[PDB]
Image: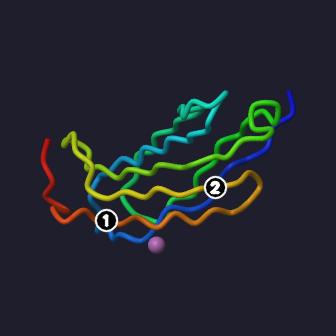
Amino acid sequence: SPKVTVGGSVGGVSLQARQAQLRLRLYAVVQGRMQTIAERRYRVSGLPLRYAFDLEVDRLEGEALYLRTELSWVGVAAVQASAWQQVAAGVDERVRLVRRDCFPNCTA
Ligand code: NI
């Protein structure tokens, strides 16, 4: 089951030592439906963060892929910053977080 890596770095906000989570969801249209095909969460206290999904090429073949990246604070169930972009396998994909207007004090 040969695999290729969809990976890169997440940056673009300063966490300043605050405990955070990054939730990365990889989307693809699978027979015409937009679906999450993979998800990772990372616990971090600074950026940038290097990420990687190792996915079967059989699963990736022919697919547009989209990466949804969401920063939250640990202890607060709310998105503080996020990114949405098309990505491609085997490419170092730079994810640049965009702060919400309510950052860093967004609420659940
Ligand atoms: Ni950075």
Q: Nearer the viewer, mark 2 or mark 1?
A: 2
What residue is drawn where x is 42% and y is 44%?
A: 23
Please give the count of numbered marks on the rendered protein.
2
Farthest right residue in view: 2
| Side (left or right) of 64 relative to 79 | right
Farthest front residue in view: 32
Secondary-structure class at tag 1: loop
Characterize the local packing of mark 2: few (<14), some (14-19) or many (20 or more) Cα atoms within 10 angstroms.
many
What residue is drawn where x is 56% and y is 40%?
A: 27
Residue 57 rendering spot, x and y as whole percentages? 81, 36
Judging depth in this view, the residue of 107 and 63 nearest the camera is 63
Q: Is mark 2 within 8 Å of ligand 1?
A: no
Characterize the local packing of mark 1: few (<14), some (14-19) or many (20 or more) Cα atoms within 10 angstroms.
some
In this view, 43 is above or below 85: above
Q: Amino acid at mark 2?
A: Val
N-terminal label among 2 and 1 = 1
Mark 2–mark 1 CB contact (< 8 Å): no
Residue 93 rendering spot, x and y as whole percentages? 63, 62
What residue is drawn where x is 65% and y is 42%?
A: 53
Which residue matches tag 2?
87
Residue 48 rendering spot, x and y as whole percentages? 48, 65
Which residue matches tag 1?
15
Q: Quarter of the image containing the N terminus?
A: top right
Secondary-structure class at tag 2: strand
Residue 77 rendering spot, x and y as whole percentages? 21, 39
What residue is drawn where x is 51% and y is 59%?
A: 49
Q: Find residue 100 and report its image quarter.
A: bottom left
Q: Is mark 1 within 8 Å of ligand 1?
A: no
Q: Quarter of the image containing the C terminus?
A: top left
| Side (left or right) of 34 relative to 65 | left
